[PDB]
Amino acid sequence: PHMGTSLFTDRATNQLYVLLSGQLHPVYNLTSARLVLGNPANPATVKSSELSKLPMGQTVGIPGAPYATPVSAGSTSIWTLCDTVARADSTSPVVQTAVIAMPLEIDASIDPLQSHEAVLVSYQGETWIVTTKGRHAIDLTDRALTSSMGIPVTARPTPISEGMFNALPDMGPWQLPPIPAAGAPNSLGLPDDLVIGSVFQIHTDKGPQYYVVLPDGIAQVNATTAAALRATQAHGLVAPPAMVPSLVVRIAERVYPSPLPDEPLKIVSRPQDPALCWSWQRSAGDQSPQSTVLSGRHLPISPSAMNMGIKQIHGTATVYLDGGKFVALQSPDPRYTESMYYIDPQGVRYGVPNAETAKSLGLSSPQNAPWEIVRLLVDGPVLSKDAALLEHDTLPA
Ligand SMILES: [Ca+2]
Ligand SMILES: [Ca+2]
Image (cartoon, rainbow, N blue to C red; front, side):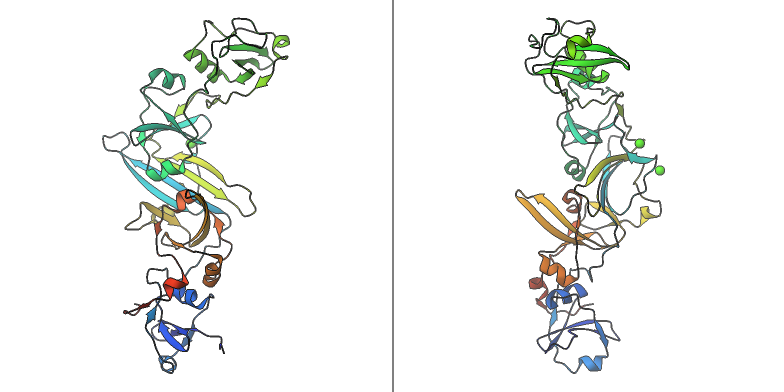
């Protein structure tokens, strides 16, 4: 019968020994011992003379596994990816990347982009504009489009890392939404001058409200969008004609999804603000995560935290965390795939193949996390019972 203790530690050496079918085996770590036992056993301390009372076998386990699988007390799952560009204005700008899995300290020196703020970046020979929503493709050699869309010739793109490029959602071209049948007569009963794609205005209590004429109705646009439309094609109008509300209220209203913000676009200076981050967060009970783009002078963590960073030899990012993590990912690989990883305090991810294995390790309720950030971590060996059952020549250290 099972006698309650299948895991032991030599009182003198603190070495681990696991009991398998009446025989002791040295085992590399607690993680491996629990994998083979099928439950998160805690070692019983005994003298070597006690261990010598059982037959001893070869070393078992996963030597590359973390010693154990502790997890930070964690209120909320928070994951942040940060690009820092060194010598942004030089002929040799360099991007460094950090993964932050811990609460942030946000201030005026490093905070979310505001709605009118944007960063011009380069990736693989192409340029993208980064806003609070993600990245938008733009070709800067198209001087007129670029200018109309609020981007000055004084703007210099700076490189983003591959990880940041993957993390930032492609929200579509930085352009005015194309207007079908632009230039053609309106079908809305408006004056002949107001062709499809033209801009008019009506006077309100808050002053002028601008509209664009669409094939299926009229849509409100802000002043910036109105100017951008007219800068591209004014349709022969010196200014947006003033219309009477009696004429306009009768027409179907539509939505024109211009990406241009109300205020003049402010292009952040990378030398001033070398840090660009994508921060992702989700609390237990939440139906959706919330994500935002940060821009500032350094990482959004305390100065004390700025040197608890760890970079793996074969990792791309320096990792900052407040303890271990147990996370659940969902990704199209290319089919919708749910996966689980344990992340050790060193910033290595280890696959947890199924719920049964998680239970063996004493891991429960994995936090939802973004694969875009988590899979940037170095991938260690999968934590499986099959792997842990393997015998080895050499004793644990
Ligand atoms: Ca600062
Ligand atoms: Ca700011």
